[PDB]
Length: 166
Length: 165
Image (tube, rainbow over all chains, first blue to last red; front, side):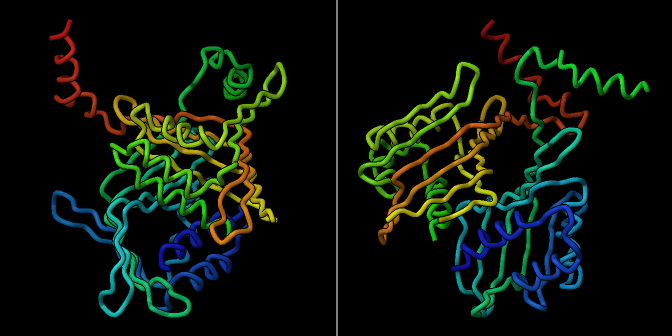
């Protein structure tokens, strides 16, 4: 099933530590992407639709640089996807795809990048992704929000202030 | 694999429509939980460890009441889970996520340690749900551009309130 393939992809990405070499991202791609795969991000903007497509060579470096900012976690949520055979492949067309990233210091902001992801799989034993096309339709940066009043009196926060003046 | 069963539970949760009648939750719990089952919440607080358990009878009413606050989406993320007539999945990094709507649109991340026991049947339903709530975050959507504060729509939200003074 192509569905699982993402859950697999998702879970394989949770496997990434802060030491992961360029060889690991290569293995990642060789696991999930065809030797000919292409990944495109589409924005339908004012001046007209802008597309950025990258080749198999930079697909591993693309996922590698998604984590660069001290990011801790990247995963994808597919809601109400569509399966169908088209262009001699299995295709999943999900209108509600959430590309999620998790950040660290200082904001710990969670970024939800949503739109229409259109994935093309081969009908192999491997079932790797031939085409990744993501049409970014929304964008959110969620901020953790102070929950209690006495949190503003934390010595640790006041310590950070002192430390900057030093 | 027991792991899929949650991805299934999750994928089924996106199916909850805005009406989802009490029968709909009846089927849900009957799909994933044994006719026996327990759902437990653990809080390790000052006065000591605090627990809340509900029986198979209340399992649907619990998940049904999870959505009540205008919540739109419920899902669980298992990170680095560990598996081992009882399969147990012991996930130390379990994130229960709910999505809220008007007016704050906050994403709630309730994280902790989830311990699930599944039967060795073809169906593989949950006998024991055990969740130890250890972190909690309320994420807020954040206005990204300056001019968003000058939107006529936000100013209209103001005007619309003054009319019902």
